[PDB]
Amino acid sequence: DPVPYQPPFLCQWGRHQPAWKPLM
Amino acid sequence: SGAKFRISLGLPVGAVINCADNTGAKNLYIISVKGIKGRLNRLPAAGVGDMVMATVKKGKPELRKKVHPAVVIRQRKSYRRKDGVFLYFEDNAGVIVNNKGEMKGSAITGPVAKECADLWPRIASNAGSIA
Amino acid sequence: MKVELCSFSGYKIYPGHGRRYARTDGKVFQFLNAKCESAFLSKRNPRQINWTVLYRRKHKK
Amino acid sequence: SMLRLQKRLASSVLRCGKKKVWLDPNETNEIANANSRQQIRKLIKDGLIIRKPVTVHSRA
Amino acid sequence: NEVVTREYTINIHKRIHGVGFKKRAPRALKEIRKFAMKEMGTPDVRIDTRLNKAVWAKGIRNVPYRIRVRLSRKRNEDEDSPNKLYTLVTYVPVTTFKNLQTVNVDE
Amino acid sequence: SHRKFSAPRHGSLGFLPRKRSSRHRGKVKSFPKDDPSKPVHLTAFLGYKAGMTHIVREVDRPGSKVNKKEVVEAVTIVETPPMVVVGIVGYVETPRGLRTFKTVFAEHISDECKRRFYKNWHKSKKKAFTKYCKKWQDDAGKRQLDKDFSSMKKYCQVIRVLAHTQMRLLPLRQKKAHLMEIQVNGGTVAEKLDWARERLEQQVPVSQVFGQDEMIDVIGVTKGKGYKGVTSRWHTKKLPRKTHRGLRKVACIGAWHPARVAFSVARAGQKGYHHRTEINKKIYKIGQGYLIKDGKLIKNNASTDYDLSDKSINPLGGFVHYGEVTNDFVMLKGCVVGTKKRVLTLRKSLLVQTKRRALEKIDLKFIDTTSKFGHGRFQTVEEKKAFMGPLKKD
RNA sequence: ACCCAUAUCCGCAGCAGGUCUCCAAGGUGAACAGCCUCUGGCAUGUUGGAACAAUGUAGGUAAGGGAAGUCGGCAAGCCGG
RNA sequence: UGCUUCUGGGUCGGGGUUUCGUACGUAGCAGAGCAGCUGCUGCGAUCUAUUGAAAGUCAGCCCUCGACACAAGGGUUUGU
Ligand SMILES: [Mg+2]
Ligand SMILES: [Mg+2]
Ligand SMILES: [Mg+2]
Ligand SMILES: [Mg+2]
Ligand SMILES: [Mg+2]
Ligand SMILES: [Mg+2]
Ligand SMILES: [Mg+2]
Ligand SMILES: [Mg+2]
Ligand SMILES: [Mg+2]
Ligand SMILES: [Mg+2]
Ligand SMILES: [Mg+2]
Ligand SMILES: [Mg+2]
Ligand SMILES: [Mg+2]
């Protein structure tokens, strides 16, 4: 049937997350 | 001669004990207990017959806003006597007593426990009822 | 050894047991257990509660 | 074997729910081959299936 | 010797002590089945709907403490099994459990 | 960086193998040292912890406030049946280690001692010691045993005796008796082995070993508590409420650059069921057991010189989770390690004990025999009946 | 014809999400608030069996002190008709 | 840890202890009172006696030698 598509990009580790942020 | 045995302690830094004499003070905020070494995150606590540092929170303005030395007489926490009785009181009570041992007030309301009366002789002399 | 009676109940308190309670006015009471302690602190009449000794002395059982 | 068809049809004939439809546990094969409202009315007249009474709700 | 009908009083409390509220009465049924398998060595134990109602009379949480059970070992009817005999478990209505022995009744 | 506010460490490095002990009976690691001036005597014993009660006694210590007062203290009842001697063992002294030389069992060995050599007594054919007991009624076997004892006169240095408990008089469920080596410290090796051969196949009571007001050591296994967390075991400080990944845990294990966790880091594991050896326990009384003469039995074990009652140390309704004590018993100050029905090793004191608190003579006044199963308020059955009166059931 | 929604729609699906409306008992109660029951419906929501270890999540209770903890009365608790 | 010396575990019951606090029924010229009949009969919360009564009590409490059946079994393995 439907071929499950490529897993949608979940914009995580970027800049809006304050979980992981290096040295600024 | 006869030293003081250990008793249960239930008045840490923060307790307001009522002042059981005729000076004029109503409350006594315990600020620190005299004679405790200390350890990380342990509140110094005072039981029956303990020399403590207090401050008159409310009462006469001559007594407020200054540090007094005090002796804790009565506590509500049940403490074990040596003969095997758990004698506990109604309220938490102390008196203002200087660094040498002499009292500031004349009379003492309420009963004074014998664990405090054997240690402090001048408090036991002014006390009418004992324990 | 002084076997003192209970204030609320009237039972024979032995020196190994009991919890003694002294008020601000005096009149030092002895209590056998926390049942009698809670009954006295909630101020119940010993002559009305059935299992006490004062109820038996009142109603002649 | 399979009596949900007969229970639904008996509820539709008796004009109530299928909770109150009491089917006969002894005569299972006699009910299982009815498969029609005309046979289920014959089962009503025979008394094999019985309308359950209403569970009481007291006002006293 | 084989066909034996006899009475017992089960104390459900000493077997049901420990379990939680939603798992008291089915566990009570399970220990009654284990009791029947314990006295009578038959794996085929068929307990009665009257005793089902007698256990589930109050609720799933409050289970009665003592109960009265007629335990009967019976020879097997048709639809034969490797289990040679079975055990029928029946409720007996008794008002008070004061001085109730395990009476071995006769047929 | 360093720690800001320095703190003492939670736990001890001396006890860090906190694993479940392999042995269940308390093994003596070190017996007291012998000296030829002292006569021969047993230096250890194996009791069973029965229960706990009060005590009332006079305190005789000069200078204290508690002088001549009636204190109460926690005491342990340890039921101590007399043990049966069923063998001896000699020990030669090697530079590698104190090595056992030759073990000589007894002729008549009771079935309670026969239980120990089998794991499953029901399937076993009870055929132990059958070819060994034939050496005591033949001419050559007695000569071989005399050669064995004559070699043990010469070459053995330490002679321990084998004694097993008497489980039949005990109210426990098990029947498998515990065996134990007890080192005899006394005179020379020949006199020691002769006294052990004289005490072979004999009862050993408790008064021959211990006495009144003697400081003893208690060896025993801790009450088991299972797999517990680090807050429950090492008693560390709890993390506050706002922690996401748990609060009854250890927050930081160690530093970065040590790439391993050290052995001293408090972790979660086994709490309870640990072999321990507590020192300096004081015996208040070695009580006599039940004995029958002139028809009626004599049971006034809790009777002191000041009580003058007929009551026993068995409380009302028996001890909690142990049963009734019928054998002779001992009564120790404080609390001892182990739960109810736990085997418990008594030992004489290693340290030369000369202290003012240790050399106090105890005179008992009152022994509380109330029902420990609940809040008891009566001492004995006749006092309870005299207080209650005639009941409905009576 | 049927589904009209914790299985018939849309969310990759028998997805704790979303979707426009009608019918509207008895007691307790101011109430269409919360709880139980009557008509109707259901098997506890992609499973169970055996023990109740540590960490947890959701609930609770603590003698004496009553914010001394913490960046901060955060959370919980007190008052409640 | 236990699993046939007419001996042992277990089930039930009985005592021992202990928790709560006086059970259903019956009686009462006890009961604030109310109603009907010429003192009696009904409603009535609560109180007293029967009644330190009733209920629970090892699942991880203590003795039973009082009734009961069970318990000398089944399978896998190992040698100088
Ligand atoms: Mg700090
Ligand atoms: Mg430092
Ligand atoms: Mg967070
Ligand atoms: Mg207890
Ligand atoms: Mg349609
Ligand atoms: Mg679903
Ligand atoms: Mg569920
Ligand atoms: Mg399900
Ligand atoms: Mg609190
Ligand atoms: Mg409080
Ligand atoms: Mg602060
Ligand atoms: Mg701070
Ligand atoms: Mg808030």
Image (spheres, coloured by chain):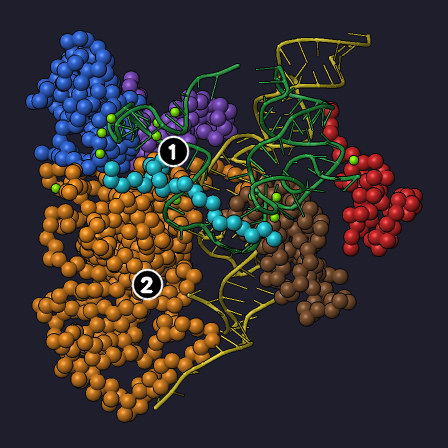
Chain colours: A cyan, B blue, C purple, D red, E brown, F orange, G green, H yellow
Image: H63 above or below C53:
below
Is the CB of mark 1 within 8 Å of ligand 4? no
Quick one: SS at disc 1? loop
**Quarter of the rendering containing residue F375:** top left
Q: Residue at x 69, y 58 (%)?
A: E46
**Quarter of the rendering containing residue B106:** top left
Q: Residue at x 71, y 49 (%)?
A: E50
Indicate the position of residue F309 as horizontal and vertical percent values: 34, 46
Quick one: SS at disc 2? loop
Viewer-proximal residue among B20 and F329: B20
Which quadrant, please, contains the C terminus of chain F? top right
Residue that protrudes farthest toward the left in the picture: B100
Q: Residue at x 81, y 40 (%)?
A: D11
Tag 2: residue type? His
How many numbered marks does the figure carry? 2
Indicate the position of residue F67 as horizontal and vertical percent values: 15, 38
Is the residue marked by circle 2 packed among few (<14), some (14-19), or many (20+) residues within 10 Å?
A: some
Image: F89 above or below F303:
below
Viewer-proximal residue among B87 and C54: B87
Residue at the spot of label 1: C33
Circle 2 or circle 1, nearest the eye: 2
Disc 2 sits on a residue from what chain?
Answer: F
Direction from residue B36 to residue F138 in the image, left or right: right
Badge number at residue F24: 2
Q: Residue at x 78, y 52 (%)?
A: D2
Tag 1: residue type? Asn
Whether discs 2 and 1 lie on one chain: the answer is no
**Quarter of the rendering containing residue F172:** bottom left
